[PDB]
Image (cartoon, coloured by chain):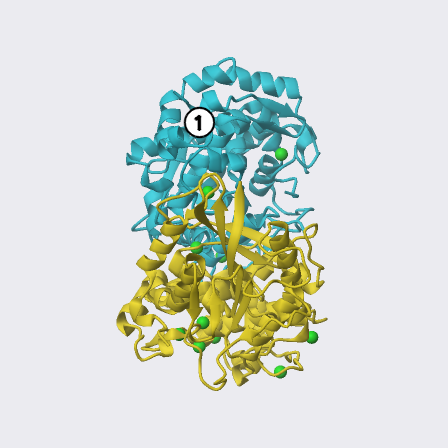
Chain colours: A yellow, B cyan
Amino acid sequence: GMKLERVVIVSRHGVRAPTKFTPIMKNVTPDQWPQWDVPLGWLTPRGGELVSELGQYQRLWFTSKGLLNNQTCPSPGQVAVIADTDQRTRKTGEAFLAGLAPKCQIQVHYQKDEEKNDPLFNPVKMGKCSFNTLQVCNAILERAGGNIELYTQRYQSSFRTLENVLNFSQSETCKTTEKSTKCTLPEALPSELKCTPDNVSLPGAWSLSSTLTEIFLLQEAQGMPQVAWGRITGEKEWRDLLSLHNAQFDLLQRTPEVARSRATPLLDMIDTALLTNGTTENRYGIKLPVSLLFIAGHDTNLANLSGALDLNWSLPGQPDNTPPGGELVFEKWKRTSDNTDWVQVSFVYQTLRDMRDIQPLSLEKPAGKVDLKLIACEEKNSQGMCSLKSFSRLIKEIRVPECAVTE
Amino acid sequence: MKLERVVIVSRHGVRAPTKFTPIMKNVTPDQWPQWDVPLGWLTPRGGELVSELGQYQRLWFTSKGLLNNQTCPSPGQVAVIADTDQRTRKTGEAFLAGLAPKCQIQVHYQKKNDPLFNPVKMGKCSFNTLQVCNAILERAGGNIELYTQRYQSSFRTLENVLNFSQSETCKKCTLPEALPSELKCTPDNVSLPGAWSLSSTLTEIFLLQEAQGMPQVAWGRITGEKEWRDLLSLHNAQFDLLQRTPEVARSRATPLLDMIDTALLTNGTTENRYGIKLPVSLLFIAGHDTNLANLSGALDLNWSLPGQPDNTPPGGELVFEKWKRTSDNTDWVQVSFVYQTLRDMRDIQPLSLEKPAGKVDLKLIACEEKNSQGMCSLKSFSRLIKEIRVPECAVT
Ligand SMILES: [Cl-]
Ligand SMILES: [Cl-]
Ligand SMILES: [Cl-]
Ligand SMILES: [Cl-]
Ligand SMILES: [Cl-]
Ligand SMILES: [Cl-]
Ligand SMILES: [Cl-]
Ligand SMILES: [Cl-]
Ligand SMILES: [Cl-]
Ligand SMILES: [Cl-]
């Protein structure tokens, strides 16, 4: 019937320590933050272990569909891995192979100038690729309703939950302020968009909240004994908290005017990997095609791909829309009856509970999987898959030619 | 006329669909747009739309003297009850975000589970399955096929919106023919599995898509208010049979009827399940469309909402006002339905006394003593609830 011929996975790095630890973070709560023994922003051994569980699940799943032969190690030119220059992405590539193909010595490709940036993951740092600053800020602004304050009103109760979790009213930030209403984060730290030719940000209570709520998720996924000082009660409060993080990523990374430019190199790689019958990747030295191309990036990249392709989703049991180790999976299926090629898009992830418990993954106890819909495709299957040329042509429409990586 | 107490029973705000099934995929060749919150959960925008109703009510209740022109309400003036679902809890919070922003008023709920909103499902009482099914079948015109005949054009409009002809299900085909409907009554639930159940769910999905402000609503194939009305008549007709039929409605609405009664009649009691000290000036209750239908059926309240195709729309509020006549110190009850038009939901229209929310003036026919302007007497209102309530379904 339907045979799986090729897969491209764009994965967020696994569980990591917080990206920063600042005076503001310390002064928005009377409590002390739990410390992490790895440096800020690094993948933890537990983060690696959770990615290996996905690697293990994907080995079993790809083998059951015939993508990889049921042998000890995949054949030469079947599996290739690309990672961004950070330790977190590089060790996610390592960790994924430890699950997928342990003791096979498969290489993790990455740029060896480890000081500099890899444009596949961050093209707007190239000279050729810059944002039209007014167009981009205004586009994000109109997605927020015309003013950030209206976007803040939309998420009021979420900010109340974050404030309750931090015990914000009793922090140094609310020391001097006394009024009829509550001391609040948005009033203490008003948010306003900042757009430059190579970057977009929303500093204030919005950026801070995005960071803090992600830290709570990371604490939980890491298996830390005291998450958010024991003050998060059930999925409702988890999603109140992570709605702030998900909404900030929506504005800064899924807004088409930003996502199109930033997702272009990854879209070009995905397209090439699914289409060609013989090519040599020039920057890493990978002989495409391969049966499985695994790409280790960040949540920013998943959000850029989501916004560019117009993919919308929610992950059962996982409050972060772009969670640690979350995989956007592009599958090339061949219909046997006419040898026509079709593309299926999925999001493979672990629930927060399965991170917390380090749930062993298999075909019996599978990883979470959400079927994604590429609605803009012209030609579709009876089973919802985009045709190969419809998939490729959608990539042509959305891509920004100035943001291509021609090195 | 002095406004002294108010009870609001509200449907939760705009939410994602409650389910996503294979039949939903197979009745159209197109793909359904995905949502970015879990199935059945309130969207942030749904929360904002409810807060606009909270703002409107703050302005309206302040002008009428119920609440004081003040930053936050005084103790024991505003209380909130919500069902255990996230969508109702969030609706309570969103409502307070508009009524009393940053005042830290609590949303009460049981720590799907609360029998105030579902007394039959939780097992307080049960339906006599034959009596309920018979009452429904008589309202259907004898059977489900006869009811189908009364909504043929509506089914044709839905099939056109779905492009049903080119669907996996058809491979001349129609929804009622391809998916025959049959009534199912069990001790805790009634349903219409088949084309009726499906159509009731799909047409609500289109309304939620539109109210959510999605770019592609029903693949852009819902043309004119006439087609909106035709589509949601299927949704509304289901809720009429399955939720407004008195044999269903009176049982399911009993806990809410008792709460409304107690909130408007007492002089002082600490309510025993949520721990609310009644009376309050405003009691807000966050329920579902099924609850509004139950109350509507039990109280024999019929309404159509100008500009709003769903009779039990997102954020729709059944409002019970206790008015005092200062002439002879007589207490009177007034019933209204407050809501937002479908366009105002899509545009997120700021509400105020200048730009008011939709409002339908309702009248309780069955009460004995009545005002010149149709209000029931407080004593008669309590008597009416005593007559229509089903004691076995009390929570209490
Ligand atoms: Cl600290
Ligand atoms: Cl660790
Ligand atoms: Cl970039
Ligand atoms: Cl403040
Ligand atoms: Cl920032
Ligand atoms: Cl960001
Ligand atoms: Cl679909
Ligand atoms: Cl929203
Ligand atoms: Cl007051
Ligand atoms: Cl019930």
x, y percent for residue B230:
36, 29
Residue B376 visible in the current orientation: no
Where's the C terminus of chain A, which quadrant? bottom left
**Disc 1 target residue:** B170
Give the image quarter of residue A142.
bottom left
- Left/right placement of residue A25 relative to residue B271 reads left
Determine whether the residue tagged by mark 1 lies in a helix, strand or loop.
loop
Give the image quarter of residue B380.
top right
Q: From the viewer's perspective, is residue A94 above or below residue B382? A: below
Amino acid, disc 1: Cys
- Left/right placement of residue A31 relative to residue A145 reads right
Please give the name of the residue rendered at 37% of the width and 47% of the height, measured from the top-left corner: B345
Please give the name of the residue rendered at 49% of the width and 63% of the height, measured from the top-left corner: A246
Q: Residues within 10 Å of mark 1 (few under 14, many from 20)?
A: some
Q: From the viewer's perspective, is residue B46 above or below residue A255? A: above
x, y percent for residue A184:
49, 71
Residue B13 visible in the current orientation: yes
* Chain ID of residue with mark 1: B
Q: In this orientation, which residue lies closer to the viewer: B248 or B334? A: B248
Q: In this orientation, which residue lies closer to the viewer: B377 or B39? A: B39
x, y percent for residue B167:
42, 32
Q: From the viewer's perspective, is residue B202 above or below residue A201? A: above
x, y percent for residue B189:
62, 29
Please give the name of the residue rendered at 46% of the width and 14% of the height, measured from the top-left corner: B146
